[PDB]
Amino acid sequence: SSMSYSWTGALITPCGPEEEKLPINPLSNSLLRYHNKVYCTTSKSASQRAKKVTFDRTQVLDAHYDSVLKDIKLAASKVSARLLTLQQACQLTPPHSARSKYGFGAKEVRSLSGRAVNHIKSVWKDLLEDPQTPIPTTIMAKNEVFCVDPAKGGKKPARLIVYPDLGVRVCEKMALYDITQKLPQAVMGASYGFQYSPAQRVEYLLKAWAEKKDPMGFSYDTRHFDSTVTERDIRTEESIYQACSLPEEARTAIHSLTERLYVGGPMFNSKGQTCGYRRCRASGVLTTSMGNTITCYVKALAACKAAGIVAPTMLVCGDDLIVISESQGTEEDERNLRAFTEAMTRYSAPPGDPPRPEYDLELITSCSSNVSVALGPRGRRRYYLTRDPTTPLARAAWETVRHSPINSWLGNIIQYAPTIWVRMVLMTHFFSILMVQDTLDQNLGGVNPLDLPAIIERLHGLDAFSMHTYSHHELTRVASALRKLGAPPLRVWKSRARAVRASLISRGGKAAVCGRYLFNWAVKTKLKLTPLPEARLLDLSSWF
Ligand SMILES: [Cl-]
Image (cartoon, rainbow, N blue to C red; front, side, top):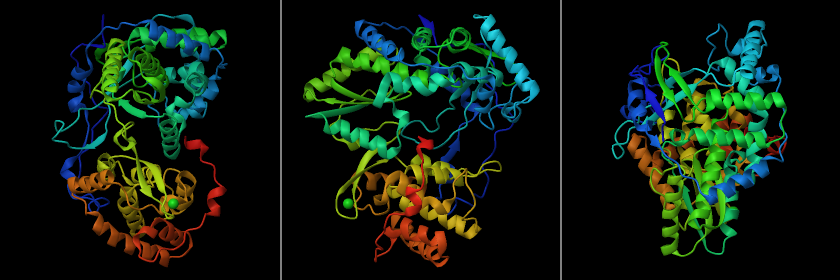
């Protein structure tokens, strides 16, 4: 039926110069040695990504799909969604969102400057007036960092990002922001994945697993998911949006954005040249995450019905899916998964690695992460979220004239606090660096490092400071990632941690509380860690 993209043959070009690694990486050359292995995707590889995501889709739906979609619209019809004022939409624009072609950017939009508001008013007018003319978009290579992997072909090519002008992006929110905030929860319930913190994600997967008499689980890796979303899926999304109770102006806007932007359009490079034409999901529109989550969910739940998955409990996150169900025995479970893959493939959601059933929760990886287990201070099993530390370590070593990795370190320390790699490696390094810089109470992206113990207790529980006897998989993977990146082994981080702990303790105050709580693992004579009052008086509902 339809190709995902066409190409004029024009280069996908950068926005200015993309920047060289340097000969010394002073913040990270004591963390790891093999800096040669750390790389950033650039436009030089955009052409190669284009090839991998340009292909034919044909889609065949069926009674199971139709039934799931019908249930979903009924669930949607219980939502009431308001327009946002132009001004509210403007205030929701992020601080460094890409500037508009019409002589203004994020700062002007967020201060409701006159010409910004004027332009947006006219953009919105035209959305109400013209429900047809395709809206132009810019195509760019994303710049992301990874560690080279010879197993899987050296260096990944850059992902492509496709987006309309800042004015339009503001309009999208006027039409759809309230929906983006209400629909997934309304349509999917506990299955909507973005509502959970790591600890909660673990709790959900564990309750799901315990509820089945003989559980089986799998993840579904979907290949270039954005490229496999069809016009029809996109129009079916509009149709789900339109099931909700909406003002009429919203409807026209939503319909018009659907037909003019979402469904597809032409793509221009940064130098202005016509680059191609798109008939799939754009990465850089407001509905991307919501859309992918909803469509992935419909397709997947239909596939479960097609394939005979019994009593399924799902967790969905854009293109990432995990399903835990009642096993029918291995021979059948293998059969049903093959049926699932066949159904998804028919629905235009074909797999990357084909799925496989598992009967141990540590062996299921989704959102690049998995559940593992360790023991707590009183001897009890403690489950937590973890992941391969390779890419976090590579990004911990990305250091240029224009980028500092310290933030990235902190993101991982918080999200993955209970892991052995965060506790023994990243935490040891982060504090060591800040101490020597004497910047231990700077403010990183809104967080004050000396509050970590509070924050971690709130997010992960006090047991995060007292876990031991990590799993074989985890010990193996962490040892192996350190070796792969030429970082010191754990043995050495332990010495470094003893030293970092001492200096923290010796400065008293919140620093010493960090030393005591965060590095209790590093000393023979364990202190008894008690709840932190500063932690009760703290609400991080905001972040998840
Ligand atoms: Cl315990």
